[PDB]
Image (cartoon, rainbow, N blue to C red; front, top):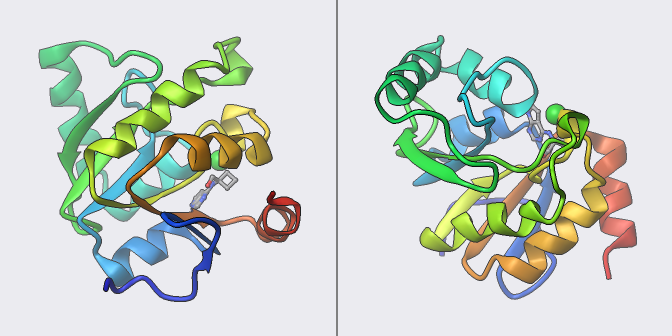
Amino acid sequence: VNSFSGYLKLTDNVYIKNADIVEEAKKVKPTVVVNAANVYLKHGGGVAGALNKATNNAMQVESDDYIATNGPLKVGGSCVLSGHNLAKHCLHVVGPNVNKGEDIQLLKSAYENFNQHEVLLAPLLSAGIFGADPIHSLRVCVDTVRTNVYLAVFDKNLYDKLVSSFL
Ligand SMILES: OCC1(Nc2ncnc3[nH]ccc23)CCC1
Ligand SMILES: [Cl-]
């Protein structure tokens, strides 16, 4: 039993809800919140900009030190950093950004990072301003993640469309 509330159950381990991931994280304070990151951990917009804003820029400060030490992530890769006031940990995961010409096949690799954590709150990777089809992202999530994932989906038209089209 966990404290996630109001989710629709899609499969044994995947759940989905129309929600602002920032507001969800503050309420639940999950062990792991997933950020829709880029390789530079520059949290400007989309989910990343919203999460970082909610941390009063502490996420960005921590991220800049991480990059200065370790260099950029790989597309499809991840790192674990602090969750600040939102979660115990933040798993920064880089899905491919179609508006940059990045290979969509890397979306499966990106979701594989979720399997290192028993329970996660997360957005749909490569959706939103990363330019991929959210229906496709949901399919890859369901077919790749085996741990318990709670998917937030801020946009309402996307959520109903995602629920109504799910196979
Ligand atoms: O899930 C991916 C999508 N973006 C978000 N989801 C959940 N919470 C969010 N907060 C800010 C952006 C955001 C892209 C379409 C939904
Ligand atoms: Cl977005």
